[PDB]
Image (cartoon, coloured by chain):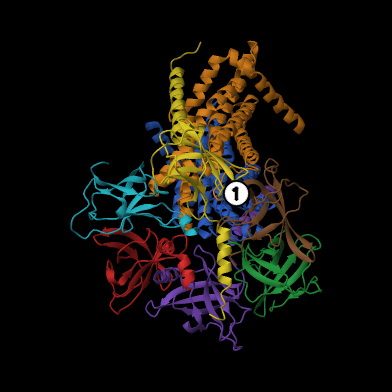
Amino acid sequence: CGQWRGIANVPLPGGPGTESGSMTLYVQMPETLALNANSRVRVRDVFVGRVRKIELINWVPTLTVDVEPGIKLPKNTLAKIGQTSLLGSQHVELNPPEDPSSELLRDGDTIPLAQ
Amino acid sequence: RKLTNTTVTAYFPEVLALYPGDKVLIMGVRVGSIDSIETAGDKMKVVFHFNNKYKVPENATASILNPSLVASRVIQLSPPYTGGPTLRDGAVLDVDRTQVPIEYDEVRN
Amino acid sequence: MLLTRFIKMQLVIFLTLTLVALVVLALFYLRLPTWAGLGMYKLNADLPNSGGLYATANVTYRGTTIGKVTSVEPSESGARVEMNIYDRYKIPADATANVHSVSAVGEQFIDLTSDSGGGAYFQPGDTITKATVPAEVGPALDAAEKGLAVLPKEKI
Amino acid sequence: VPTYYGQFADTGGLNIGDKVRIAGMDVGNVKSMEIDGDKVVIGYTLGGRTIGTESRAAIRTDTILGRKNIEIEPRGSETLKPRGVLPVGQTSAPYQIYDAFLDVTRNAAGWDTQAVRQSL
Amino acid sequence: IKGTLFKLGIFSLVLLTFTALIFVVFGQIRFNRTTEYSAIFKNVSGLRDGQFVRAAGVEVGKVKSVDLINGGEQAEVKFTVERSLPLFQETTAAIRYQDLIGNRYLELKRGDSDQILPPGSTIPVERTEPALDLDALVGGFRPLF
Amino acid sequence: LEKPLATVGGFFKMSVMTGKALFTRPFQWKEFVLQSWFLIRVAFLPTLAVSIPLTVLIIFTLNILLAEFGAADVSGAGAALGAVTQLGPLVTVLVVAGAGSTAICADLGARTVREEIDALEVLGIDPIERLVVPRVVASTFVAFMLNGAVITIGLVGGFFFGVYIQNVSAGAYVSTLTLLTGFPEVLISVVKATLFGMIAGLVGCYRGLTVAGGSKGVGTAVNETLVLCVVALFAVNVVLTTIGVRFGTGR
Amino acid sequence: VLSGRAGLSMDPGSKVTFNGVPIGRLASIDVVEVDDNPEARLTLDVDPKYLDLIPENANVELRATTVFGNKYISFLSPKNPSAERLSASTPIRAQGVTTEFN
Amino acid sequence: RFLDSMGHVAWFVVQAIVHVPHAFRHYRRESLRLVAEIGMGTGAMAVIGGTVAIIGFVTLSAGSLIAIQGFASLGNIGVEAFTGFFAALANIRVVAPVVTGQALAATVGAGATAELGAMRISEEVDALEVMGIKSISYLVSTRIMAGAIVIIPLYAMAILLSFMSAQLVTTIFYSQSVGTYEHYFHTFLRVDDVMWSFLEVIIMSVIVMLNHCYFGYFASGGAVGVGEAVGRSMRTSLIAIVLVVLLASLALYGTDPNFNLTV
C-alpha cells in the first residue's frame, strides 16, 4: 500500500531469474532512464534475468537483479542500461570487461557506481 | 458529380501508393479527390478533380506528398491563387510541372 | 402437401437475397476471380535475394497494381518468384523486377520497370532474369557506426 | 469559449482537434481551417486565456509519426479581442520531415563522391 | 435471507474490490505521503498533469498542475515529491521524453550542494531545461541540407 | 408501425413509473437482495466461461499479428484497450441478455400466468414498486460487478496466456497496460455496464409483465426479450463507444 | 548457430531465412561458456526441405529487418559453396551481428 | 448422474445425426417450410425482417465498433492508414464469426427451443409417436438440415454487412480516403481466412442447433418451463460458440499466422 508503485513495478512470477539457484545482485546505477521493474537482464544480448526492485537509497538508484544459475560473471562486470528498440522496451546489459578477473560475483554481491 | 468541379489531367514518372479517391489539397486543405490512374507509355496519367469554389493558377505544380511515415499520399497544388489567369477545365499537366515523394528505397540507397 | 404460396414467396426472396449476397461478396469484396486467377496469366522472376518479398504481395508497374505475387521460394542462385498478372496489362520484354518497400514499417512489393515502355511483350509463363534488391538496413547501420567511430574526437 | 483566428501560409498537415499550446502546456484546440485566398485561416481557442496582439503562432511537428500542434508566444501589451486574427507575418510553417529527407537524398544523389574523396 | 445476505455481501465485496483494483491500476493512484514543490520552465514541451516525477530515473511523485506565468512567457509546474526524499539547493529539474508518442516526465538531479531546499520552494528557470523540441531539430537541418 | 410504437410507449410509461416509484416510494431491501443473488447465480459461471476463451482468442490474435508486425512489445497496450472498452461491456451484454434478462422475463411471466400479479393487485399493492424496482436495481448492480470481473479476469488471463505460451515479455505487458487506457476508458466502461444492466432489467420486467399466457406465451416472451435486449444493448454500446472515444486518452 | 552476441530484438519465433526467403524459425537462445567466455547459441527449427539447398559453407548473419522491427537469422550462399549439405551435426558460426542503436 | 447426462445428450445428438438422410429423402417439404421459417422469422419478429434483420443490425453494430475504436486509436498514435487492414483482421478472425453466432443462437436457437417446448407441452410429440412417426427424425433432424442450409447465406450477409459498415464508418464518418482503405483491405485480406471462417461458422451453427433442439425436445413443467429451457439453451450456446471459435483459430493459425508485413 505505502510502497505501491503501480502494476508495472510489481515483481512477476516465471521467466529467468525466478527458478531455484538464481543469484541476486545489486547494481548501483547513476540514473535508471525511467526503467521499470520486471525488465530484462541480458548477458551477451540473451534474456537471462529479471530486475526485481529499483528502490532509491540515499539518492542513488540501486537495482535488485535476479539472474538464472549457470552464468559466470567476473567481479568487475560492466552493467549498462540500454534501449532494446526504438519503439520498444529497455534492458540491463551485464557484459564482462576486456580484462575479466578470476573472482566471480556471488549471491548478494554489489556492482558499484564505477562499473 | 460532374460539371460541379474542375477536372485536371497530370502525368507523372511514378505513382506509388497513390490510389483513386485520394485527397487533393491546396495549402493543406482538402479541395477535391482523384478520379483515375492509368499507365500511358512510360508515364502515369492521373485524372483528378477539385471543387469549383476554389481557383487555381494556370501555372500550378501538382506535387504528390507523403504527409508522414504512414499516411495517404495527396496531390497538392503548390502555388496558391493570387490572381491572373486560372487553371481552366480539361488542362493537362506534363512531367515538367509535377513532383513525386523521395521514397524510402532511394533514401536507403 | 403445404405449398401455401406464402412459404414459396419467402423461399424465392431468400434465394434471391442469397444469390445477390454471395455474388457481391465474391466479386466486389473478396475478389474471387483475382484469388483464383481468372483472366490472369502467370509470370516468373529470378532474384539474387528475396529482399523480404512474400506471397500475396502486389505486383506493380510504376507503382500501380497489375497483379499479385503467388509464391516466393528459395533457389540455388537466389529466389524464384511466381506471380499472376491481369491479361489486360502487357509489359515490355526489356523490364526489370525491382523489389521495393512502401514505407519504413514494411509492405514489400515488386515493381516491373521499363524505361522504353514499349516493344516486344512478355508471354505467359516467361521469366524475368534482371532484378535488383534495396540496400539492407543492417549493412547501412554497420557502415554508419564504423564511419562515425573512426573519427578522432579529441582531434575534433 | 471564445474562438480566435490566425493566418497561415500552409496548414502543414494540421487537423481539427490538434493541440494549441502556450509555453509548452496545452491551452486549446483547432476548430476550423478555411482557404481565404493566399492564406489559410486556422481558428482556435485559448481556453479563456489572454494573448497579446503581437503573439507569434507556429505550426510545428510534435512527434516523428506526424502529429502537428500550434505553439503561441504572447507578445505586446494590447489584448487580442475574441475572433481576432493574427497577421500572416507573425506566423510560420514547419519544416516537414519528408521535406528534410527529400532535400538530403536529392542533394546526396548528385554528388560526385570519388571527386569529394579525392579532394579531402 | 441471512445466508443469502452473507453470500451477496461477500460476492459484492470481492467484485467491487476487483473494480476498485481496476481503477487503481488504470488511474495511477498512489497512497504515499508527498510534498508539494514548484519549478519554472521557459518551455514545458507537452508536460501534463498526473505525469510522473522521477528522481534520477526512480519515480518519486506526480505532477499536480502547470500554469502560465509572466504573461505567458514562462510556465510554472507544481509537482509532488515523496516526503522521504529531500531536495537540495542545487537540485535541478528537467523534462524528459518517455516515448516517441508524446508522453513526458519530470526528472530531478540531486546536484552537489548539501543545503536542504525547504519544502514548498521554487526551482528557478536558471536550472530547468526543456525536452527535445523535435521541430527545432528538424528545422535546424534546413540550412545544412 | 402503430403497434410497435404503442408497445414502445407502454415500455416508456412503465420505465417512468419505475423511476417514480424508485425515487418516491420506500425501497425493497429484501427483494433487491434476493434478485441480486439470483441474477448473480444465473450469470456468474457463464460469464467466466465466455470471457476466458474470448480474451484468450483476442490475445492470441493480437500477439501473432504484432509479432509479424515486429512490434510485440506493445502487446499489453491493445490487450488493455479492448478489454476495458469492448470486451468487458460486450461480454456483459451477451451474458446478461442471455441469462439475467431471460430469467427475469420468465419469472415475471410465471407470476403473470399464475395470477400472482392479480393477487398482488387485489390487495391494493402496485406490482411495479414491489417487483420491478428491486429487479432493475439488482440487474444494474450485477451488470456493474460482472463487467468489473470480466475486465480483471480477461487481463490476467491474457497476461498468463501470452507469457506462458507465446513467449512475450511480462514487463512489456504489465508496463504498457496504461499506455492507451486511463480514467476515461474505465469511466465509459462503468457507464456502459450500468446502462446495459438498467435497460436489460427494464426490458425483461416489461416483457414478463405483458406475457400472453397460453402454452407458448412464456417462451415467445423470453425469446423476444432476448432479441430486444441484444439489439438495444448493441445500439447503446455503439453510441456510448462513439461518445467515449470523443474523450479519448490518446488525445 | 554460435555467435559472439545474440543481438537485441532476437527472440524465439524470429524467422530464419535462406537467400531472404523464410525456411524456418528460431527455437531458442542460450548462453554457453566457451573458453571461459559467454557466447550466444541459437537453436533453429528448420524444415528439412531446404537443407538440400543450403551448402555447408553458408554464411550466417543476425541481420535486422527495419529500424523498428526485430532481427532475423539469414543464410547466404558463399562464393565457393561446399558440396556437402548442412545437418544437425554440422557446427556453424555467424560472420557478424548488426550493430545496435545503442 | 453427470456421466448419464452426458450419455443422454450424446444419444440425442447421435440419433439426430443418423436420421438426417431419412429426413432428406422423406421430409423435403418439412425442410423447405423450416428453411423459410428460419430465413424469414416467425411470430411478431417476422414483421421486422426476422433473423436476417437481427443478424444485419448486430453485425453492422460490431463493424461500426471496430472501425470507430480502430480509427480513434490509430489517429491518436498517428499511423491511421492501417485501419482498413486492421478492420479486416478484426472481422474475419474474432468479431464477425462470434457475433454472428451469438445473434443466430438468440434468434433461431431460441425460436426452435420455444417451438419444440410448445410441441412437447401440447403433446404433439406424443401425437407424432402415436402415428408411428420418428419424432426426433421429424423435428430435430429437419431443424438441423434447415439450419445447415440456412447458415451459409446468413453468414455471407453478416460478413458483407460487417465489411460495409466498417468501410462506411471509416471513409465517411471519419472522412478517410476510400482508395487507401480499399487498397489496405484488399491487400491484407486472405480469402483462405474467409473460407476457414465459413467452415467454423457451419460447425458452430450445427452445434448450436443441436443444443437448442435438445433443450426444446426435453422440456417440462408446462408453459413456464419453456422459458427456463430457452435461458439454459442460450447460456450453453454462448459457451459453445466461443469455445468453437477459440479452438478453430488456435488450430488454423497456431504455427503459420498467415500474415506478412515486414521483410
**Disc 1 packing (10 Å; few <14; some 14–19; many ≥20):** many
Say left or right for G12 vs E121: right
Residue extending farthest left? B84
**Colour of chain A in the rendered structure image:** green
Question: Chain B colour?
Answer: cyan
Q: Nearer the viewer, residue F225 or C36?
A: C36
Using the image as rendered, state which of residue B22 and residue H96 is in the foreground: B22
Q: Colour of chain D?
A: red
Where disc 1 sits, the SS reads loop
Residue beneath the point at 56% across and 37% down:
H193
Question: Which kind of residue does numbered mark 1 sit on?
Answer: Gly
**Tint applied to chain C in the drawing:** yellow
Q: What hue represents chain E?
A: purple
Kindly tell me whether residue G60 is visible in this rendering: yes
Q: What is the drawing colour of chain F? A: blue
User: In the figure, H81 relative to C35: above or below?
Assistant: below
Chain G rendering hue: brown
Q: Position of residue F55 (x, y in %)?
A: 61, 47
Which chain letter goes with mark 1? Answer: G
Residue A73 image position (x, y, % from top left): 77, 69
